Length: 104
Image 1 (tube, rainbow, N blue to C red):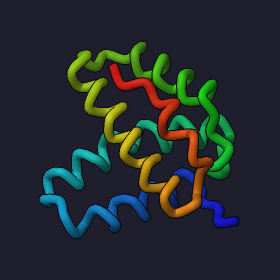
Image 2: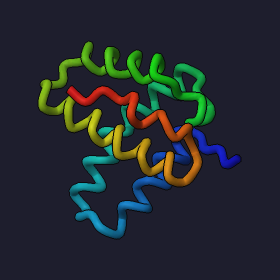
Image 3: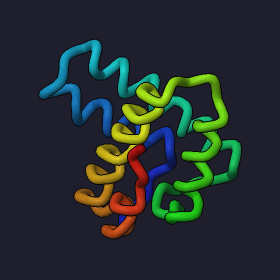
């Protein structure tokens, strides 16, 4: 039923974690997800529920094509994974989506 755009979902998640995470962790989450929000918006993804295993794989490959180190990429995908778990809990995305996130 509920629907959130990438930006809305990103802001919601950061506020949600703004209770059990240090300021630096929130910033890290913000920096990591910033790449996803811009990518999703440019790819015309207007609602997080629109995400699929294919789109997630496209994103992973896109990031793998950047100048980021494997260690940095892993932490980025892990945050992406935790983000989707949160959204799945609040009915914003399909319950079987977070599992489709590949964390190298």
